[PDB]
Image (cartoon, rainbow, N blue to C red; front, side, top):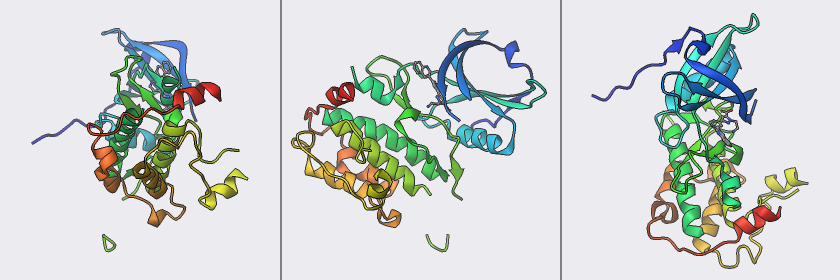
Amino acid sequence: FHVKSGLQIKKNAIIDDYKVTSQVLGLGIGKVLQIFNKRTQEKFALKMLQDCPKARREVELHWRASQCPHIVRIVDVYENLYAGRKCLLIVMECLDGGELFSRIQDTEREASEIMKSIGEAIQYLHSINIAHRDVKPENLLYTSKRPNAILKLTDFGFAKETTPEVLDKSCDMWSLGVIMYILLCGYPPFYSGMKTRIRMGQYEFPNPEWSEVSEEVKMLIRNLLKTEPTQRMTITEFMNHPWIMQSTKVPQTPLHTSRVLKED
Ligand SMILES: NCCn1nc(-c2ccnc(-c3cnc4ccccc4c3)c2)cc1C(=O)O
């Protein structure tokens, strides 16, 4: 009988429990500040919203999704006044490693593992009927600069509850597709009309980036970047796909991604 706790929105001053600093760890809707837990002294990330109903949706949905290992954990949520302005302050696990591609710029097998982790993130969300939507790289961060460090998904501002016929997340699978692409070659499939080339499904696999790359991956990216959503791959299928399912038995084929990101 495994029952996790509910969302306690603490009403007391946040400054009673943490010391809020200035250092901004990200801007994204509303700066994200680094703060320290008075009791433990661990670093945490604080997100501050105006207490409207959209903002209570983010909290709710993030919180529900927080148990997933590859989704930035929420540690507590506060309702405070601030210049006569009711607010939702979210406290999250501090992901020190920084943004996915920054860390890149410093192999196929490595590509896969990263993609696996991001899949589990979506798999979880989908299995509890949450679409994330805004699954860009800017919202994919590592827990530490350490190489074993693990990749976790953030930012639920655009997340939405989806709640087989007689019983929206399709676009998360697009994001995955795109994120896969960039990991391999090092640049988007739709370089800068770009809006008109996306609607056509108009992208190449130009060499030398994609010369050494597998047909197995190609066809997977292809299914992920299908223009028509209903044609596009499901999360469940994605995770059953051998390339993703078997990261322990995948090619260690080198790609010049770090080179390209440092380039552009
Ligand atoms: N993705 C940008 C916006 N955004 N960033 C965060 C976030 C959450 C947790 N940790 C960080 C974080 C912490 N330390 C860092 C140190 C260096 C570089 C980036 C860092 C990012 C950032 C949350 C949100 C959000 O939920 O809106």
